[PDB]
């Protein structure tokens, strides 16, 4: 598994995701940290969000376990940083890379999946009163991620 | 002058008559005749080798009743 | 399963350009000469050994998410 973790690390260097950084924290290659800048033209614009990335022993046959460390107001992300994303659990494939996951997360922030939510109350605001949904998200971006 | 099998597609079957001297590119056209597949859609594989369109059944050493493997490429998988 | 032995395999030869798959997406390694390649029903091929492990637990083409039994 090591060999493929290193492969991805170069792939990130040659084609870095838009305003995103990721890599191992220390000598252990299986534990990385990542940062994502809140997408422009989203409620999160201007925020910096930190993530943990943990590669399973038999990666890439098991997907990586990814989670936020920064609090975020979002229908698919909970107060524990858990992320409701399909590629991370049941649509996982060896063909997927760390870059693709980061870009999926990045697009999830732009466009939640309120029909299959992780936080009902915020999903319900997103569909029915989007204007309130963004102000709160902007507020949270301003408060814990700046 | 020789029986050959190309049972593949998962809907496998097909029995063909051929001469050892037949080039692979004759084979793909006879598969177009038993089946509707355009030849350029066809990828023939045998004993661990792709078969080159120009080479023949004798070249590759396909003996009677050899049962061979067809793979269908698509217009944009 | 036994199904994994019912799919075609063929040692890669760089000289002949019949498929446009120059890479095994599970290993992220170019196809090297004589390496064993396994092709799935959907005409997607990877390193045989490399994709073999994935079929034990799953049954979908890693690239296009198509079943392969
Ligand atoms: Zn490989
Ligand atoms: Zn496929």
Image (cartoon, coloured by chain):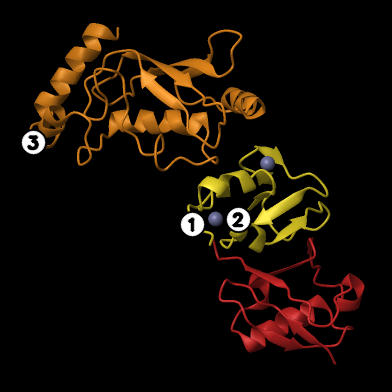
Chain colours: A orange, B red, C yellow
Helix, strand or loop at mark 3: helix
The tag on residue C66 is 1
Q: Percent x, y for residue B70?
A: 67, 71
Location of residue A135 with respect to C27 vertically, above or below? above
Q: Which residue is mark 2?
A: C44
- For disc 3, the marked residue is A128
- Dot 1 crowding, Cα within 10 Å, few <14, some 14–19, many 20+: some
Report if the CB atoms under discs 2 and 1 are less than 8 Å apart.
Answer: yes
* Residue furthest front in the image: C2
- How packed mark 3 is, by other alpha carbons closer than 10 Å (few <14, some 14-19, many 20 or more), is few
Is A118 situated left or right of A99 in this image? left
| Rendered position, A133 above or below A80 | below
Where, quadrant-wise, is the N terminus of chain C in this rendering?
bottom right
Which subunit holds the residue at mark 2? C
Relative vertical location of residue A101 with respect to residue C68 in this rendering, above or below? above
As helix, strand or loop, the secondary structure at mark 1 comes to loop
Q: Where residue A75 sits: x, y (%)?
A: 21, 29
Front position in the image: B56 or C68 = C68
């Amino acid at each position: 598994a090591l060999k493929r973790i290193h492969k991805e690390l170069n792939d990130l260097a040659r084609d870095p995701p838009a305003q995103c950084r990721a890599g191992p924290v220390g000598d252990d290659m299986f534990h990385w940290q990542a940062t994502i800048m809140g997408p422009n033209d989203s409620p999160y614009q201007g925020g910096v969000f930190f993530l943990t990335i943990h590669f399973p022993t038999d990666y890439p046959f098991k997907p990586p376990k990814v989670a936020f460390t920064t609090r975020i107001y979002h229908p698919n992300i909970n107060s524990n940083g858990s992320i409701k994303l399909d590629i991370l659990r049941s649509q996982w494939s060896p063909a997927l890379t760390i870059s693709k996951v980061l870009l999926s997360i990045c697009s999830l922030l732009c466009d939640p999946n309120p029909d299959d939510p992780l936080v009902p109350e915020i999903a319900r605001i997103y569909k029915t009163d989007r204007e309130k949904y963004n102000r709160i998200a902007r507020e949270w971006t301003q408060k814990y991620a700046m | 002058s020789m029986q050959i099998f190309v049972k593949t597609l998962t809907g496998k079957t097909i029995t063909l008559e051929v001469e050892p001297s037949d080039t692979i590119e004759n084979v793909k056209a006879k598969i177009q005749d038993k089946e509707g597949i355009p030849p350029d859609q066809q990828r023939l594989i045998f004993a661990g080798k792709q078969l080159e369109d120009g080479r023949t059944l004798s070249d590759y050493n396909i003996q009677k009743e050899s049962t061979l493997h067809l793979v269908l490429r698509l217009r944009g998988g | 399963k036994a199904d994994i032995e019912q799919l075609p395999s063929y040692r890669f030869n760089p000289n002949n350009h019949q498929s446009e798959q120059t890479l095994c997406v599970v290993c992220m390694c170019d196809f090297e000469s004589r390496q064993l390649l396994r092709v799935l029903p959907c005409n997607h091929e990877f390193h045989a050994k490399c994709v073999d492990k994935w079929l034990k637990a799953n049954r979908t083409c890693p690239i296009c998410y198509a079943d392969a039994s």
